[PDB]
Amino acid sequence: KCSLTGKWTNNLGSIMTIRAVNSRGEFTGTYLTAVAANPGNITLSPLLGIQHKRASQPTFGFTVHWNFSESTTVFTGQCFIDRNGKEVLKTMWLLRSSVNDISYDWKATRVGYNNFTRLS
Amino acid sequence: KCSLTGKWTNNLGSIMTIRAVNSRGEFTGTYLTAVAANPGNITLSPLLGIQHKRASQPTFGFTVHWNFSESTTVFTGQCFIDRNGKEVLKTMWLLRSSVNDISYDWKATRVGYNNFTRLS
Amino acid sequence: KCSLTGKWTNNLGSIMTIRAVNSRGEFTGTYLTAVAANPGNITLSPLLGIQHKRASQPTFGFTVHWNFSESTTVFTGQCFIDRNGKEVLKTMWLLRSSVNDISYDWKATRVGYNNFTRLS
Amino acid sequence: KCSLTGKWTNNLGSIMTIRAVNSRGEFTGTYLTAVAANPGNITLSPLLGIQHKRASQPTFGFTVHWNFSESTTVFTGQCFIDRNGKEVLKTMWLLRSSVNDISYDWKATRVGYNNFTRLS
Ligand SMILES: O=C(CCCC[C@@H]1SC[C@@H]2NC(=O)N[C@@H]21)Nc1ccc([N+](=O)[O-])cc1
Ligand SMILES: O=C(CCCC[C@@H]1SC[C@@H]2NC(=O)N[C@@H]21)Nc1ccc([N+](=O)[O-])cc1
Ligand SMILES: O=C(CCCC[C@@H]1SC[C@@H]2NC(=O)N[C@@H]21)Nc1ccc([N+](=O)[O-])cc1
Ligand SMILES: O=C(CCCC[C@@H]1SC[C@@H]2NC(=O)N[C@@H]21)Nc1ccc([N+](=O)[O-])cc1
Image (cartoon, rainbow over the protein chains, first blue to last red):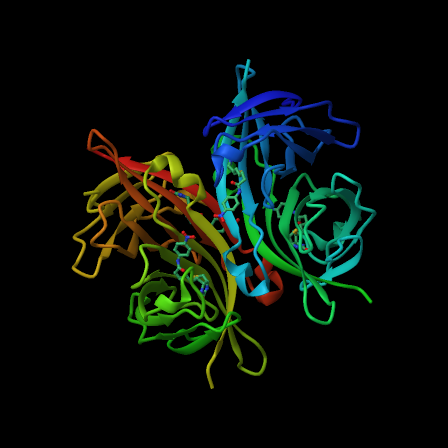
């Protein structure tokens, strides 16, 4: 069974820590991004998400509320466990920036990927 | 100030309720999608997210754990208010399907938009 | 049969012309965006794409080489025709900005939607 | 200067071949995908795109008209050259499937990434 609780790094060097997953699949955690628009401002930020519970290789999603920006990121993906028991989170994300009014809405959403593996 | 708490509909005819937003910007709710891969199977599904608390037109994200599928959707966007006080959530989403192993990961993520308005 | 050749406008107020589609489904045209990072700089920009030729409601893609920026957009979508013969292009796009090196790549891709209808 | 003409592989094992880039930045080529919904049907497929010409690390886009499917993919990205002259294409893509009518449009667009390096 592919589990999400614990510490993970991604391909950009970011670190996240996920706490206990409850019986609904809900989890909280923290996210330390390696990169930002203004990296001098980066602070540890909270995340909240839900995974599927029954599945051995669950899909999941989470939201990161950046504590140093008006932006928000959401990640979704799947936890895969390979034949040797190694886990990988394959994810894609949307990063929503804050714009001044709806005329700027079109430029406010970035997309990308991240692959996560366990810290230890 | 653009508020997320309440009842919303989107351009596909889906509806959602969002409950009270706490001091950290966290919220729960319930999502009824109008569409699915198998629409005959649709059940009400929980959502969990975070918005920015201080901003007049906050960015936010939330995860929907579909209760009738192994998939998960994340939404992110911004709440805008026009001159007459009418709110719109401008959002982008990623829908993650469950695939068998990492070699199928490439086809597992759909993307789209949704615009939400308040019901009454 | 839903045809791409002609003059189109989208929900942001941008317009494009698409020229004749050849036997391979290839087409050129000209795009006038209503919006940019720097709207004072906007110039007409060429597009180049391919549609499926046989399909009544073809999928397609095209690239816009912005003539006033180092960025590029790609659009993909499908041409639908309703019962009265009215066409709509339902599209999704990626806007790639130029960044200095690979360490900035994560923030270089925006995503969004556009719905196009025929001008007259 | 980061050039696109030549043969490339990506992280999924796909191969593409780009021909001469003209003075406008337009190029054609072929794409042999390693993966598909129905891999038994895969055939070499044409692509058409545009890159920026002046830039040492140009952004670009291209469309692949799959010759074995009603779907279309668009790719956009940037060509980076590192301190040793090694080139990488960092891309993201949208894959548009053909659906029967507009009520299914919401599920028709997949998103993902690909990193390309030169075959030789
Ligand atoms: O910089 C920020 C906030 C931090 C985002 C980090 C992103 S989350 C996706 C990716 N995966 C990671 O591990 N880290 C990165 N927000 C921001 C960025 C750009 C703009 N902008 O206007 O361009 C505005 C806000
Ligand atoms: O059908 C599902 C679950 C429901 C998704 C509803 C989407 S959320 C984005 C959009 N906005 C809405 O209000 N409703 C739609 N999942 C699913 C679909 C296809 C496949 N598949 O394998 O093809 C697997 C799971
Ligand atoms: O502004 C630009 C070039 C023009 C992009 C217009 C986009 S295409 C998707 C959407 N549909 C339309 O009809 N129009 C918009 N590029 C750009 C923007 C921002 C940055 N940046 O660094 O922030 C760099 C280049
Ligand atoms: O399978 C197809 C056509 C081939 C697409 C190959 C994709 S292009 C992005 C990625 N990078 C690669 O090098 N190769 C893959 N189309 C398709 C897929 C799924 C569905 N579907 O309905 O699920 C319909 C058509």
